[PDB]
Image (cartoon, rainbow over all chains, first blue to last red; front, side, top):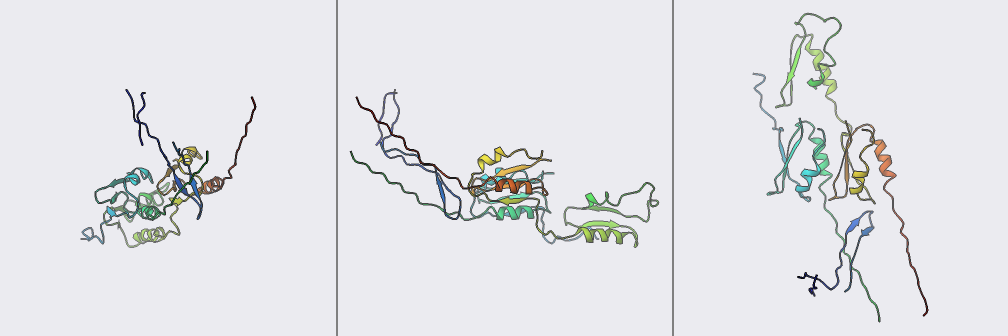
Length: 39
Length: 85
Length: 135
């Protein structure tokens, strides 16, 4: 869901924001600069 | 009589068609091989690019674009979490 | 070629002879052929050179495209800007993660060695810390 705080306010999200960046290097290997949160 | 010859194929400009990469990035990545100069133009509406540059060393471009148009594999990522309180 | 013929067969400290019995050369860019005019024991030389000049390339090395395996190329473009500086223009693709070298066609070996020493699997370390107290 998404909920607004008073900072007149803005949009705020609460959930599981899982994002990554995959880089395939070798025949078989990968690189993952991942970040996320369960809120 | 000698000058007035017929052209086998006009190579002053030749139009290529790229298969897997877009051409927007390629125009700007490729600006400076041999620099009169090489003017690369990209269409975007048929997704094909031109080469109106040197009519003799274009082979140095066919080889590089051929090494630059290639199917790309993609990877499936899943993460899992769990806790107890 | 013609841009490079009147430098190899141009003149001497004393002229071979008056303006005749010696050929001049121009060319158009349109049909990719070259023009000569002169005498039946002058032109044969010109055809000799072009027969020699008109050789086939073992492999075009003016530009060669490498593929780097473990490092990205974004950092590498900017880290590598100034070996020998006409200049060396390094371009990086980013969409296949490969980089080019359209620079000197004779000392590239000084680049193959360095990139080979610059693409290497990297080990990673596991860190855990612990704390505890009593009140």
